[PDB]
Image 1 (spheres, chains in turn cyan, orange, blue, green):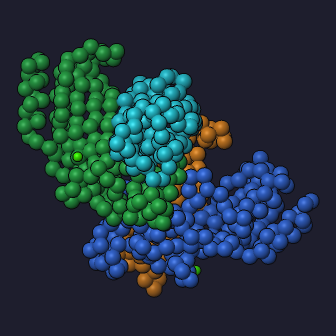
Image 2 (image 1 turned 90 degrees about the vertical axis):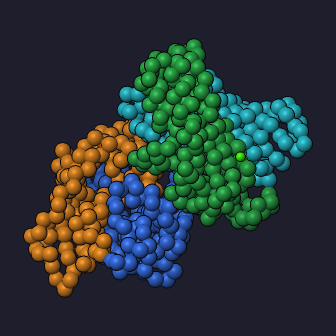
Image 3 (image 1 turned 90 degrees about the horizontal axis):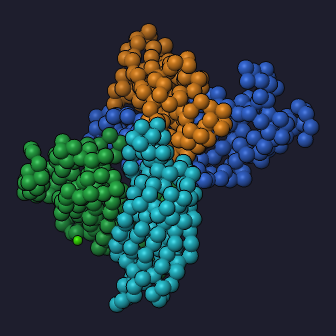
Amino acid sequence: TVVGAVLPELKLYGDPTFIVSTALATRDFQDVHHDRDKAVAQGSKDIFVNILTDTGLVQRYVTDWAGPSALIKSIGLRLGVPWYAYDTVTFSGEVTAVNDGLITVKVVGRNTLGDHVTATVELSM
Amino acid sequence: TVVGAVLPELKLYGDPTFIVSTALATRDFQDVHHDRDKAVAQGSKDIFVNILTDTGLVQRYVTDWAGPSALIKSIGLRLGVPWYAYDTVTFSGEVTAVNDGLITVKVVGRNTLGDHVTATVELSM
Amino acid sequence: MTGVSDIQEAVAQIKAAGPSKPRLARDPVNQPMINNWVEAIGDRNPIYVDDAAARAAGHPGIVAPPAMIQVWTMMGLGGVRPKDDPLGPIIKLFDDAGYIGVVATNCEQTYHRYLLPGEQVSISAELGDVVGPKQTALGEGWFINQHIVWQVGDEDVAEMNWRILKFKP
Amino acid sequence: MTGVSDIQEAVAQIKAAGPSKPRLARDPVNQPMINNWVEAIGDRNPIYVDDAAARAAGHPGIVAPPAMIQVWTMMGLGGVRPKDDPLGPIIKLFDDAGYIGVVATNCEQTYHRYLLPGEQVSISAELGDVVGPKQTALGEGWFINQHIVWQVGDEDVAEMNWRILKFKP
Ligand SMILES: [Ca+2]
Ligand SMILES: [Ca+2]
């Protein structure tokens, strides 16, 4: 691949089943990802996607494009606006670096509230 | 044990985390056990405890009393009023039969709405 | 098609197809899912989590909770029943006849023996008695029984007879 | 006790205790929990679920998703951190100083290799740089870094550097 190559888009609808099932599949039982009343009590609008799911989706997004042979070396997240129930995050990608067979991808996940997550991913072929 | 023996009481608070975590631990992803808006849309007051969790609690309630050596032979449920978020179910028990080393227990789970579940359990020592 | 004698005939037609072909559980009986379940249910019974303890009560080693039998073969997120599951045709039949509502009324499970981690379960389903029309608190309806058998290989290890009410609201 | 030079001293005191003693994951890397995760995440990468496919890409057999590393050692329902986890003291320190709010800001994970079903992971945590006080959109606060290492036995297999902001709302 080349620097400046853009990954295919991926849009994900954050319905409650998605938010709850991903949080519990990452064994994250914090009430903010499945209990709306506790989320609201703690000052959030609704339940929201957890950080481990962010990591997993970023990983998925890059291997969706790179394919099965890709070896994920690192995933770096800068956390942004919340991904609340019924919001849609759009992942966009751009290759930023290629060197010694080590690829670096900048990933941004955007929803209605703005930039939900910014990610730097390092991988092999 | 003897016919007419009463089991110790067990009260369970159905907070959302309990309702959601038990449903997903029984691999029941129906939206009525974790998505309040879908539950309300389908005519329910709130999310509610699923039937597989009922079965599991009835089992737990009887082995809590009978102990580790008990062999559960059968669990029969007659389904009653819903167990909604924030309602408390009280399990009460009564031994109804003893014969040939086969014990039969009648279990009732009661909450504010009334009889949530009625159960007949058969076990060995 | 049209009416009660026709509903009886359709039920008989579904039954004539016979039980669904055995469907294998996603996973064998396994300790991580046992752990998730006893964690959430709050059942501290030692025999589900401790090999040594699952012997004072007379088992070989850790056994799965009997009430987990249905968990192993749950369809999962977004799963769709196979075509030969009689549940499908029977719901479709009664929905079309106007009995659009549904509630479960009874669930009876029988456990022939305890299962061990590593054992893999299959499920087969058959239509049982279909009774109706009857007048109920929720309206006129038909009570439908389904009979489920779980096997480890060719060994019958558990079953479930459960009943739903399909009704006119 | 009282003030910034004292907060710096307290941070140094926590660091002097050293990293938490390795805590073992509830389960080994295992296929059922991999299945739950790829199911929910919607990642269809064949190497997580098919031994044969986890070889065309060059692995021995099925490998766990790298991003699952933190999942294996999650505390679980109602779990409580051990006393030697520096996270505890550091939150307590800043809460008492009035920096009662918290948000995560950065999470960086490094994967030295892929893990295989059956491998069992341990986790150790250490306090990294603590920087403050700083003026932020959420108010005055301190940025706290924590450094996590995962091992299979004595082999370093992954790490996480993550950062939180403890602030006055
Ligand atoms: Ca049988
Ligand atoms: Ca390292």
